[PDB]
Image (tube, helix red, strand yellow):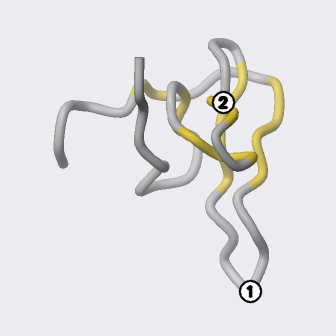
Amino acid sequence: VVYTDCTESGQNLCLCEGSNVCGQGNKCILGSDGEKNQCVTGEGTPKPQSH
C-alpha cells in the first residue's frame, strides 16, 4: 500500500523515516524545533483517513 507522512506526534502507520512506515507499536514524533521525523517504539494513535 502507499501511506502518507504523519501530521501530529505520537501517531503510527505513517511515513517517518523516509518511505519506511512507523510500524505498529511505534509512533512518529514530528520534530518541534528543526528536528526531523523520528519513529520510536512505545504506542501511538493511528492516523485517520484525512485530518
Residue 34: percent from left, percent from top: 74, 86
Q: Mark 2 belongs to which amino acid? A: Cys
Which residue is denoted by mark 1 in the rendering?
34
Q: Is residue 11 rendered to the left or right of residue 26?
A: left
Q: Residue 41, how many percent across, how many down?
A: 82, 25
- Looking at the rendered structure, the secondary structure element under dot 2 is loop
Q: Position of residue 13 (x, y in %)?
A: 51, 25
Q: Count up the numbered dots.
A: 2
Q: Which three-letter amino acid code belongs to the residue tagged 1?
A: Gly
Instruction: Name the foreground residue: 31 vs 17.
Output: 17
In this view, 35 is above or below 23: below
Please tell me whether residue 19 is drawn above or below residue 51 in the rendered image.
above
Quarter where residue 20 is shown: top right
- Observer-nearest of 28 and 15: 15
Q: Residue at x 67, y 53 (%)?
A: 29
What label does residue 22 carry, if any? 2
Q: Position of residue 14 (x, y in %)?
A: 51, 35
Please tell me which residue lies in front, 49 or 25.
Answer: 49
Mark 1 Cα shell of 10 Å, populated few (<14), some (14-19), many (≥20): few
